[PDB]
Image (cartoon, rainbow, N blue to C red; front, side):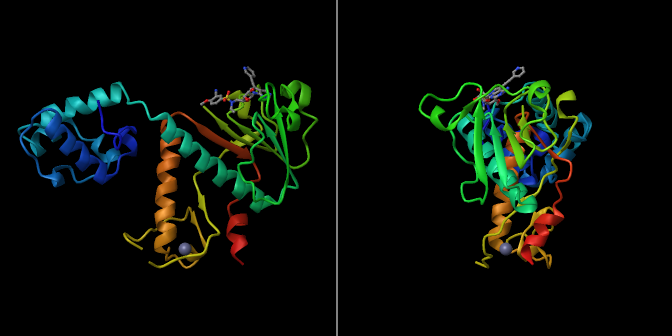
Length: 264
Ligand SMILES: CCN(C[C@H]1O[C@@H](n2cc(C#Cc3cccnc3)c3c(N)ncnc32)[C@H](O)[C@@H]1O)S(=O)(=O)c1ccc(OC)c(C#N)c1
Ligand SMILES: [Zn+2]
């Protein structure tokens, strides 16, 4: 049992998440009321305290809270499927949009897409679809193809390849990948970043200091309120996807400085 605002692993919890954890546990287990600032820290810090630190901070429920956390760690909550679908779509659009802008691939080979739907429909690129089992109502614009590196490593060399949850034996070097370690040898892990080219708007909040917020307003280090809100929503989606066991990989020459250069 857990609120839908706590289903992520405690490592990703914010300081506000911890306070909600305390209030939820206060009601679920009929514990003595506890001040929210008793555990004024985020999740990664809360996981470093000892059971004794819990007892000192909360004499009346410290031991109980500690054991509750250990069960949450031993049996993690399952995320909502629709929420995870939305998160995955947001990440897919962000990453593929950025790669196309950064490196201006003339062609995208979407391998494992059975519905012929572009995740970045506005991009200036030739979009091609392949799938081993295309949907009957979209097969007329999908190449029926089971990708295997040993068979196709000399194909799809122009442009970039997208494998979104298409768990092939081994990815080509020019690929963008989401997968739920030998398969990735031609690639590198994709570090987190947020990119936006939408216009800034002034009406901040808690000021956002982050080198990974790639926005025009961040060139000067002062992120506008709109992009700060977008960044935080995107990070929540990214974390939800990472917590659910997905990992992102990319062609080795992917470079975020190419994204910064789009603002000049
Ligand atoms: C649209 C995404 N899907 C996958 C799509 O890729 C097609 N496909 C699969 C492939 C495979 C494989 C393989 C190779 C070695 C060993 N064993 C399996 C292959 C392929 N070689 N070439 C083209 N096309 C493919 C498939 O027809 C489908 O359309 S999925 O199945 O909905 C899905 C969703 C979420 C997931 O995880 C959260 C997972 C997982 N895991 C899968
Ligand atoms: Zn902005």
